[PDB]
Length: 337
DNA sequence: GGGAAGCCGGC
DNA sequence: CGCCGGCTTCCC
Ligand SMILES: [Ca+2]
Image (cartoon, rainbow, N blue to C red):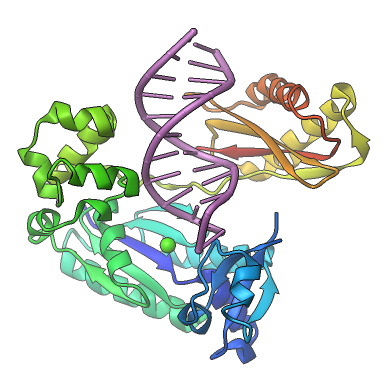
């Protein structure tokens, strides 16, 4: 398999500089409100210590010279959509992982030769750069997971590569904390059990391991540690779809809300097109503007009716638990196929 | 079935 | 930047 993973560097900030070039070379911080937080920081801003998730208040007191802009999501979606469309032209299959990440299966495209894959990846960085002035990072590897890992090692504006010949040697010297699913709490204690690198997984009690990691993840690590891990690039998009409609007025009455919720399972569902969700979320935004959501997960796609049936059920649950008044109601679909 | 808990990771 | 939206597993 030949996977190219493409990661748009600090995408929201890059989009702002492309739109407003006078922002280039000065700190720029993109802000998100739900006090607000940093969604993205450009280079000069990051260089001063501004990080994603940081409260705007703390950011200002380390980058007072930064320009702080509000997040303009619809326009970032427009750029992303365009770049995704550049991508799928070069791919057999493309998995959109988020607004700024995509995995391309180009196996059948470079006629199976990893070398022409690397060059394809170059052409792809250059194309995006010429046409959209967006710099991206790419990783080229035999699978999705390796492609990502080496991509993150190559930040920013990079091109990282793990040749099929190098896979085993690479997997071997790989620290355990560099592995997705392995956060701080359990890296800490895989270390306490003598596991420092992914190879150490091979030489361990599978039961003393299992009891802290979990069955499915122990499996994951084993399969990974022996180059027997491979999940395919599914041709799809993981970006949640849905819309939230503003109501006539505040309401906590199930029957007043019900049709509003029912109509959102149209205004979005038409735009949903071919893809089929496994998860439903009713999103309620209070008069307070707080977000109250009840999601459920079903190992089955979602017909128009399977929504309604579980829709109001979840709307119930929301009303039956929160006391706040509700101003807008909506729906979010995820886990597509 | 589905809520509580712990963990990961994106923001 | 330390917090809370998805997944997995424990528990009732
Ligand atoms: Ca990233």
